[PDB]
Image (spheres, helix red, strand yellow):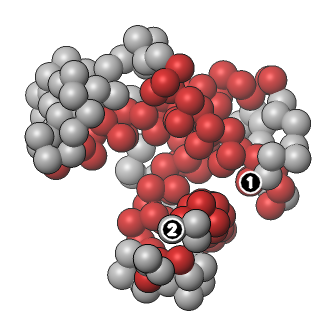
């Protein structure tokens, strides 16, 4: 996917998608019960990466930026053209719109599955250096119980792409 030049015309759309991914990364942790704290911990139910998109440093925004870039690059490599078409938290208000209403087409579901497959392949390539974790197998040879979580995590990219116009 990295062999594709990213069109600057959709750079703002990519940044918006990264912001949406980040705010989802906030909401899921908050639903789990996570607040905003200065310590990067998982058992203490706090996360220092729940602050506004503008206040995010380069040490915290690059992850969502890169997910947006790789999602759009993977879509372009697949072939479909890309172009023009509440719980009270501890400081952040992630709620762009109601993006869970329009039915996602089977084609877009398949593309979301392809994005999940690509992400899992990259993660497995990273993880083969560690032993013998059972998840080192490709996404096709993976257990079907955890496939839906990754597919849902990758669906919101195309969801935002369709909703934003």
Q: Is residue 44 above or below residue 49?
A: below
- The residue where tag 1 is placed is 74
- Tell me, yes or no, whether the two marked residues, 2 and 1, touch with CB atoms within 8 Å: no
Q: Residue at x 83, y 30 (%)?
A: 7
Point out residue 83 in the picture as x, y percentages from the top left corner. Answer: 78, 36
Front-most of 43 and 15? 43
Mark nearer the viewer, 2 or 1: 2
Q: Residue at x 58, y 66 (%)?
A: 129
Point out residue 89 in the picture as x, y percentages from the top left corner. Answer: 15, 27
* Element type at mark 2: loop
Number of numbered discs visible in the structure rendering: 2
Can residue 120 be seen from the camera position used here? no
Q: Residue at x 88, y 47 (%)?
A: 3
Q: Is residue 12 above or below residue 136?
A: above
Q: Tell whether 125 sits left or right of 87.
A: right
Q: Residue at x 39, y 51 (%)?
A: 101
Front-most of 84 and 79? 79
* Element type at mark 1: helix
Q: Tell whether 86 sits left or right of 111.
A: left
Q: Quadrant of residue 117?
A: bottom right
State the mark number for residue 130.
2
Mark toward the start of the polypeptide (2 vs 1): 1
């Amino acid at each position: 996917t990295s062999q594709i030049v990213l069109p600057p015309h959709l750079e703002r759309i990519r940044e918006r998608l990264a912001e949406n991914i980040h705010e989802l990364w906030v909401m899921n942790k908050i639903e789990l019960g996570w607040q905003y704290g200065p310590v990067r911990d998982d058992n203490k139910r706090q996360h220092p990466c729940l602050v506004e998109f503008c206040k995010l440093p380069e040490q915290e925004r690059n992850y969502n930026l890169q997910m947006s870039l790789e999602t759009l690059k993977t879509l372009l490599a697949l072939g479909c053209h890309v172009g023009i078409a509440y719980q009270l938290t501890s400081g952040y208000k992630p709620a762009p719109m109601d993006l869970s209403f329009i039915k996602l087409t089977p084609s877009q579901e398949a593309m979301v599955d392809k994005l999940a497959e690509n992400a899992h392949n990259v993660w497995a390539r990273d993880r083969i250096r560690q032993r013998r974790n059972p998840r080192l197998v490709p996404y096709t040879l993976l257990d079907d119980r955890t496939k839906k979580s990754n597919k849902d995590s990758l669906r919101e990219a195309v969801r935002t792409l369709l909703g934003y116009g």
